[PDB]
Structure formats: C-alpha cells, structure tokens
Amino acid sequence: VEYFEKLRSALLDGVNKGRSLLKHLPVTRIEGQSFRVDIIKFEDGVRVVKQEYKPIPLLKKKFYVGIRELNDGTYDVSIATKAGELLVKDEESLVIREILSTEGIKKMKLSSWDNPEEALNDLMNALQEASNASAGPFGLIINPKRYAKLLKIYEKSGKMLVEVLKEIFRGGIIVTLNIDENKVIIFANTPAVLDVVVGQDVTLQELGPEGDDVAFLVSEAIGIRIKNPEAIVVLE
Amino acid sequence: VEYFEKLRSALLDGVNKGRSLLKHLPVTRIEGQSFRVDIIKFEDGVRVVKQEYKPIPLLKKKFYVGIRELNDGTYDVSIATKAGELLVKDEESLVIREILSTEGIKKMKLSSWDNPEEALNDLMNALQEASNASAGPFGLIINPKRYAKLLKIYEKSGKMLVEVLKEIFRGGIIVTLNIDENKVIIFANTPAVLDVVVGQDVTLQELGPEGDDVAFLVSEAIGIRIKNPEAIVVLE
Amino acid sequence: VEYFEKLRSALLDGVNKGRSLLKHLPVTRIEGQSFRVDIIKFEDGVRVVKQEYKPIPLLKKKFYVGIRELNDGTYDVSIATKAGELLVKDEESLVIREILSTEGIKKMKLSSWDNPEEALNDLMNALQEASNASAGPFGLIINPKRYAKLLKIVEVLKEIFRGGIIVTLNIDENKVIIFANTPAVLDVVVGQDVTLQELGPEGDDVAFLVSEAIGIRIKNPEAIVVLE
Amino acid sequence: VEYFEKLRSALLDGVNKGRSLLKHLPVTRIEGQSFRVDIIKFEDGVRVVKQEYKPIPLLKKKFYVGIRELNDGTYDVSIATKAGELLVKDEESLVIREILSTEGIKKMKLSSWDNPEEALNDLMNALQEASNASAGPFGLIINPKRYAKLLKIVEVLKEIFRGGIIVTLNIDENKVIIFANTPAVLDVVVGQDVTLQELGPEGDDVAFLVSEAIGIRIKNPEAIVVLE
C-alpha cells in the first residue's frame, strides 16, 4: 500500500547518499549467479590464458518497522535509509576488499603525502606502472584523509594539486570512506580491465510480521571481476 | 555475424585510445607498399640531395576468441582491445626506432632532469639546434618517466615546468611509453620534415577456426618519411 | 506465482513415483476429518456387525526454498520432490503401522526362513488362514530382506498372491502381512489429497507445506494375517 | 550445404544409439557455462544444506571428410557416426568419473565375486546403505566383466534394482556403483546439446567439430555407493 513505496523510496535515497565507488566503476548487468573471468595475455598471439568462474554473493540488510507504527502512519522511514546506507557500506567494502586481494595487482610504497611533490610522485609512478597494462583512462580511489592532502595550491598561480591530478587521472578521483586511509588504488577505469558484475539490483522485500513488527529485506547481488590485474596498482 | 562488428569496434577503439605518436605527427595516406623519400638539403640552393625508396612493412597482431564463447555470446570483446592496444605499441615503437636510426639527425647530451632548470635548458638548446634546419612548430616525443619530471614546479617561475615548455614548443608534447626513458626527441613537427605514410589502415580480419577458437588478424602498413633529418635532434 | 505450479508438480510427480502399497489398495474419498468403519461379516446374510469411528490424521511434510533462488528462478524443484518422496514414505508406513495394530487381524508364527521348505509353508499357511475370511485376491507385504532370503530356487508367488506383492522397507523386516485385497476387507479413505501450501518467508527462504488426510478401514480383520 | 544436414544426422543417430547411462539419469537444461549444485537433505524439513558452483566442461570430438568426397557426394557419413559414438563414450565415462570423485558418496569393500553367495551380498549391502539416504528406485552401474562373474545361477536384479542396470565398459571393471536414481539425488545438467560445426578446409579434407556441454549434479551423495 503506502508504507512500502515510501520505505523503498527512503531506502534508495539512502543508498545514493552513500554509494560512490559503484557510480564510477564500469558495471555489467549479468543474469545469473556467477560470472567468468577471462584473463588474456600474449603467447604467440593475444589469447585467453586462464579462465575462472566466480560466484556473485548476495548482500543483504534487514530492517524492522513496528506493526503499530505501520498503522498509525507514525513509522520512521529513516529506518529504511539507515538500512540502505548500511548496505552500500558493505557493497563498497566488498569491491575494495576484493580488488585488494586479487592476485596480480601491483603494489608500491605509499609515502606520507606531506609534500605535494611527494604525493604527486607516488601517484605519477603508480600511474605509469599501471599504464603499461592498459591505456584506458585512469582513476584513483582514496580516503578523505588523503584527499585532503591534495587540497593544496600547487602552482603559485592558484591551481590546486587536486585540480592538476584531475587532469591526469581522467578515470576520476573516487573519494570513499570505505578504503583504509593508508591505501590508494590506481586503476584503469575500463571494462576491459575492471567490471562490477550485477546479479540482482537493490530490492526491498517485505518479509513479514515477525513479532510486534514487520520484517523487511534489502538485498543485492554484486561482485567485481578484475580482467587485468596488471592495470591496477595499490599504494600500501 | 555480430561478434565481428563488435570485436572490430573494440579493436579500433582500444587502438585509438592508445595511439600517441600517430595523433600528432603528420600523416600521409599512400597507395602502394613502399614510398620514396626525397631528402631535401641546401647545397648551392635548396635541392634534393639524395633519393631513396623505402618499403612499408606490415604490422601484424593476432588474437584468438574461443569458439564456445563465440557461440553462446559470452566472448570478451576486450581481447580485441588488448590486441589493437598492443598493435600500436609496435607501431609507435617502429616509428621511434626508425627516427632514432635515421642518419642526419643531430644528437645532444641529455642530462638528468632533477633540476628543472637543466631540463628547461637541454630542451631550449635542442630547440635551438633544430631551429637551424626548420622553423616549423617544434614538438617533442618523450617518455612518461621524463614527462613527470616536467610536472614538478620550476621554482624560479612558480609554474610546472611543462606549463612553461608549452609556451615554446607549439609542436606539441608527445608523451609515449615507447621511447627509452632516457631519450628525448625534439623536432620540427612539419610535413616538410616528418611524415608518417600509411599503406594500409588498421583492419580486423577473421582468419578462421584454428582449434577450439577462431583466429583473428589485426594489421596495418605504416612507416616514417624523414625528409629533413637535420630538423630532428635527439637528447640521449 | 509461477514457481508454485512448478514446485507443486515436482511435488506430485514425486509422490506418484514413490507410492507403492497405496497403489494396490482400494481407495475412497471422504469429505471430513473422521470416518466410520463398518465391520462386514456374514451372519444370515452379508451384514454389518460392528460400527466404529476413526479420525483421519493429517500427514505433513514441509520444505524450504531459498528466497533468492525463488526470485531469480534458479530454485531446484527437486526439493519439492524430496518432500513428496518423504510424504509418501510416511503415508505408506502409517497404513502398515495401523494394519498391524488393528483388532481382529490374525497373527501367526513367522519362522526365520533358512530352510527353504518352511518359508513357502509359512506363507502358504497364512494365506490359508486368510482365505477363511474373504476369498478375494491375496496380497503380500514383506520387507525386502525377507524377499531376499526368499530367493534360493518363488516365481509363482505372482501366481498365488494375485492381490499384489508389495515389497517395502516400511514394514519391519521381521513381519509379513498377507491380506485379502478387497473393499470387503480393507480400503484407504482420503480426507484431503496431497496439497502444496506456500507458508511464507521464514528466514532466508520461503516455507512450504505438503499435507494430506488419509487412513485405512479394515472392514474384515480376519482377512488379514501378520507373521510376527 | 546438404552434406551437412546428412552428416549431422548420422552424427546424432549414432549418439542416440550409443547412449546408455545418460538415458536412465534425469536431465535438466541450463543456459550457461557453470551451474549451482544444491545439496538437498532433511533437517526439520526438506532443505538445502550446502551450495556449490561447478563449471560445465566442454566435450568435443572432431572428424574429417575428404574434400573430394564432399564434392562428388561419395563421402561416408559413417565417419560422423563414429565421431558421435566416441563423443558418447567420452560423455558417459565423464559422468561416471565424476560420480566416483564426488564428496559424500559412501564407499564399501567390493569382494572379488568367486563365491556366488557373497556377490549378491555385496550388492544387497550397498543397496542397503544407499536406501538410508533416498528411497527412490536404485540403479546399478557395473562393468560387463562383473556382470559376467555374476552369471552362475541374478534374474531378480531387475526386480530389486528398478532404477536401471547400466552395464558399461566405461566404469573400471573393479568398481560398482549403486545409486538412488532420482532428481532428489543426481541429475545431468546440459549446457549445450550435441552440435555439428563445420570448421573448414584443413589439408585435403574438411574438418568438423562435434561438441556438447554436460555435467552431473550430485545433490545427495549419501544416496550413492561405490564398491571399490
């Protein structure tokens, strides 16, 4: 009836408020429960060296709205929000946790970033190493605390280091709180290397009266596939 | 016959997004499999000092798409991408190696670009040298590793060195990965000096079923015509 | 929605493939929860000698199918099948259990068949005692282990036990039932056919309930003989 | 052109005549390269106890028909048949190979049948252990050599092993499989039916590729018993 369309709406408008990583990476909507990871390399021609099948896990958060409240009209839609808001935090964390564990991605030394010069360096180096794999536009994923270290006037003119970096990393600068403050991901933002496989979208399901309140289920099928580890660099 | 038009597109794109040299040097669409270089010089007048016929070699790069995947439609178009992406690496590498080997080009001492001022000099001096042969806009082919040094701020000016170098060198700053980190080419970016002749564009040809997969052939005819060796100077 | 009708079917064509005893016994539909059992004997005419009311107990079996699977259509209908298989097993052993505990049924001494001339005897003997009640075809309900020891030559059982030779692990290995297969003797009364009900979301999966009402009426106990 | 449709047929009506095991097992179509295996057990209801993803491997067999023959129409379609025959043999032994290497399956001691009273025992025993998992009909997969030594009287196997008696040289002579033939236990999942593909001119003949995607899902390992 009502309490639904409203709850679901507040669920989504709470998912967007916290979703960032998934707004920039390339997403491919699959129809299944698992996907294949075709790893291509060069041996007497560019061909698929290793094939691998990975399952798309199910992400879910459940929220409960009082029965009574659902009838008074006195229910707090913000519950749904805290739910979705919480979903993406896991969704985002998943992606990052996987990229970081993927076998193949290159790892380099992440410095302090107190001298723009120093930070710009780390980035420029990571960027090169990665470019060797794919020319595709490059972007980086960083935590606010680091992002801040980039908010400095670089050229006596007035251009901030960030602004310069934005011209270099056309893949975008993804700032998320879900990545450890001391880890930076440099990557080719191209489906030919990075791919967020979507098995099931985000959906609100009304389980049902489980106590003095109704139970609800927010869930989504999601997973990333790294087709070209070589094109990703992690600054640890 | 859709898996083709798709692969070709992925190819052509990846090829394009990877080209650097071929986007800035001047190109001439030739006809045959060879071209003639009329080397122009000044000896009691501007005249053709030496004629020379050069053959345009064929650049090949082949990829294989599984048949299974080709049938159920789960083939990864990204192979075509990596393919062409790789094609250029040879295509550029060729042109570069061929310039560097051409006799007549001038060579100067390339220092370590740690003190922007030195770099700014080397470049300004190479500029001078080339300026003797031509006058046409001057540009430079340079490896990302060196280009980065140019992003540091030239203290005495307060701008990134690059930003200054772009004031001189209207020929463009070609940054390619296909030129020894420690070799820089300054040159007159003019058809009257440099010239990339293309015998055959980049094309995707479906070789044919060879095992469990289908073979494909990415290929192109290409070469550089250097008419004024003296308008090219290599910092090595 | 749709995964229902599909589960429902796998449920049935799992119950139908599993039924054995219940395929040989006569059946009657009754709309209710209890039924009346009429003991039919001959005393100056075929007459009803004793009345008696029994309740048709409910047989249930539940299964759960993941929520996800039900949504993305990748659920394994076999689940329903397994449910049905079990339902039947319970249903079958229930009938047997109840026959064995009915009033009049005649009991004889079953001898561990090791000396193959006594085996055929014990059967032929029971089948005799049975015949004294009702002449209708005779059925045999024996555990497979007994049907095993019964192989040492047995091919004419099908010639003598026309009523049917039900071999099932649902009757204690050390018991054998010989009965006159006929309405005048026993019959299955069904209060509710097998039905699939979608209970609902119950954790991470949806719950389903397979159920049926069913019982047996032994009208002429004397026509039944157990070998304990 | 036309020699295709003709080769294709000989290919099929060669695969169809050769299939054995695969004719008795239940089958399910799946559009994909991998499938999910659901372990179905009973724990307060028929429920899925374990998930797991397997990939459907590709089965291929190729044959070559002379260029000439293909042109003057004197090609021997039997070639395609032989191809198909082989495809099946590979397909069959693949299923068997995989059953034998599945997780839960119960293993028992198979005794070289030389003393005919032990033979029937080993089978009857396995068939027992199996029954404790699923009651569905039981199947027997035995090498012919064993089906040989099993002839010294065996005629009731068809009476006890209703699930089917698959005799094939595809199962190691010294191994025997007894299983509950039912979806609730195992089933074949096909990702791609048998298909004929004309690769092309490759020397003096044209090359052809026969292929198919196929695998087995053991949902209830306990319902399977190997005799090693």
Image: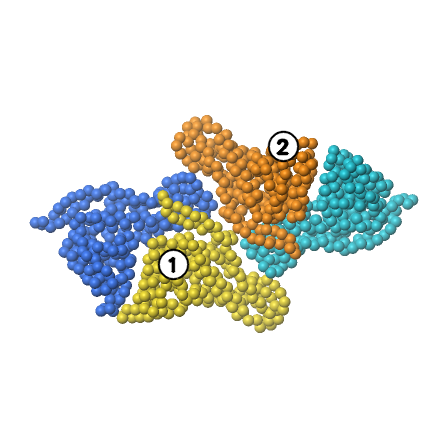
Chain colours: A yellow, B blue, C cyan, D orange
Crowd class of label 2 (few under 14; some 14 to 19; many from 20; radius 10 Å): few
Image coords of residue B14 (percent x, y): 35, 51
Q: Mark 1 points at which residue?
A: A107
Tag 1: amino acid: Lys
Image coords of residue A61 (percent x, y): 54, 63
- Residue drawn 44% across and 61% down? A96
Tag 2: amino acid: Ala
Q: In this view, does A43 lie above or below A148?
A: above
Q: Which chain contains the residue that carries disc 2?
A: D
Image coords of residue D22 (percent x, y): 58, 39
Crowd class of label 1 (few under 14; some 14 to 19; many from 20; radius 10 Å): some
Helix, strand or loop status at disc 2: helix
- Residue drawn 37% across and 60% down? A108
Image coords of residue B202 (percent x, y): 31, 46
Q: Which chain contains the residue that carries disc 1?
A: A
Q: Is residue B60 visible?
A: yes
Near-viewer residue (D96 or A157): D96
Q: In this view, does A177 lie above or below D18?
A: below
- Residue drawn 48% across and 61% down? A91
Count numbered badges in the picture. 2
- Residue drawn 60% across and 53% down? D48
Locate residue C136: give its quadrant. top right
Q: In this view, does B127 lie above or below D30?
A: below
Q: Residue D202 carries which label?
A: none
Near-viewer residue (C96 or C180): C96
Near-viewer residue (D107 or A170): D107
| A21 on left or right of B186 | right
| D17 on left or right of B91 | right
Q: Residue D148 carries which label?
A: 2
| B146 on left or right of D192 | left
Q: Work out which quarter of the rendered image holds the N terminus of chain C and state it.
A: bottom right
